[PDB]
Image: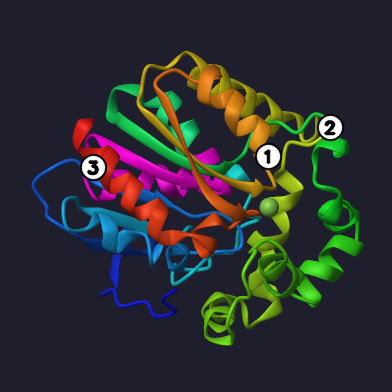
Amino acid sequence: IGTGFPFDPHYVEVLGERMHYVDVGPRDGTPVLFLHGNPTSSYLWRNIIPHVAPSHRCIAPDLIGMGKSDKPDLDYFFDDHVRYLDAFIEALGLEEVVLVIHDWGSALGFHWAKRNPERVKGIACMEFIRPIPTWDEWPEFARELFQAFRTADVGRELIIDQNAFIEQVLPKFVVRPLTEVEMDHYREPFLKPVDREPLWRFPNELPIAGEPANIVALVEAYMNWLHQSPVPKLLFWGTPGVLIPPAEAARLAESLPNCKTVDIGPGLHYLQEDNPDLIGSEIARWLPAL
Ligand SMILES: [F-]
């Protein structure tokens, strides 16, 4: 599995801040917009993009405060990310898009799709955010850790001081062993503890047990939209998963209209790190029929 990032950097000004993005592929069709989540960046898509770039433009931004994007003095609530991603999409003058989305990038993508349904031609998704009714629906192997992340003082000490989202959650949520070269890519934006705010705010935004109420409501809303939308959907899943266990992926194959699922094999949360070639090849096979 490749560890390099062989992509020319691009930057665009968004609400007075610079955002980094990958931009490869032909420029005369519907672009494919790749949205990472926590604690990753466009690096997470590095081995998937090459499958799609021969036929389609691939745009992969680094979220505000992440990757090579600028680090404004924000609290980095979900709403902050919504504002910057909305403005990034407009700054590139994108019209219709296909979304490829994961984790908080899926909350962003689904929320954008709900608000701009005529502009979404297809959605490929994996390990995406739904409301989590109770802690029992969070995997036991990561339950105490995420509960700690959401505990006053304790969570900041873990994520801000000890860098636990990078150092603990990444290896925990990839089935295969990650290499040092890969870990160093993921570490690069967060060498300075103060810069880790997004990494801590994100798990504190997860819709778990009805809290925070604003996120639960927003995620319920995009899920009601998704369950009634005719947009083509391609859902990748692994065993045992984290946010989307096998039995749930099988239900969604039916409970989401126009949906196909792809089993990537063993996988936890960062499925892109376990089977990037199957994800990329199957997205490439699915695109032309949109
Ligand atoms: F998170």
Q: What colouring style does the render use?
A: rainbow
Q: How crowded is mark 3: few (under 14 residues within 10 Å), some or many (20 or more)?
A: few
Q: Is residue 85 magenta?
A: yes
Q: In this view, does 190 lie to the left or right of 146?
A: left
Indicate which disc residue 112 carries: none
Pointer 2 residue? 209
Q: Is mark 3 on a helix, strand or loop?
A: loop
Which residue appears farthest toward the top when viewing the image? 228
Residue 266, how many percent across, how many down? 61, 55
Q: Is residue 22 left or right of residue 210?
A: left
Q: Of circles 1 and 3, which is in front?
A: 1
Residue ID at (11%, 52%): 27
Q: What stretch is highlighted in magenta?
A: 80-108
Specify the amino acid type for callout 2: Ala
Measured as percent of width and height from the top left, residue 57 is found at 20, 53
- Residue 239's place in the image compared with 275, above or below, is above
Point 90% across, 62% down: residue: 153
Asked whether disc 2 touches disc 1, contact meaning CB atoms under 8 Å apart, the reply is no
Kind of element beneath mark 2: loop
Q: Is residue 44 visible?
A: yes
Cα separation between marks 1 and 3: 33 Å
Q: Where is residue 55 in the image (x, y as percent from the top left)?
A: 16, 51
Compared to residue 58, the image places residue 43 above or below, namely below
Could one spot residue 15 in this view of the protein? no
Q: Name the residue under label 3.
A: 94
Is disc 1 placed on a helix, strand or loop? loop
Check disc 1 and report the residue beneath it. Answer: 245
Q: Which residue is drawn at 19% across and 40% down?
A: 30
Q: Tell me: residue 54, above or below residue 258.
A: below
Q: Which quarter shows the N terminus?
A: bottom left
Is residue 45 found left or right of 264 in the rendered image? left
Rounded to the nearest whole Å, what is the CA distance between mark 2 and mark 3? 36 Å
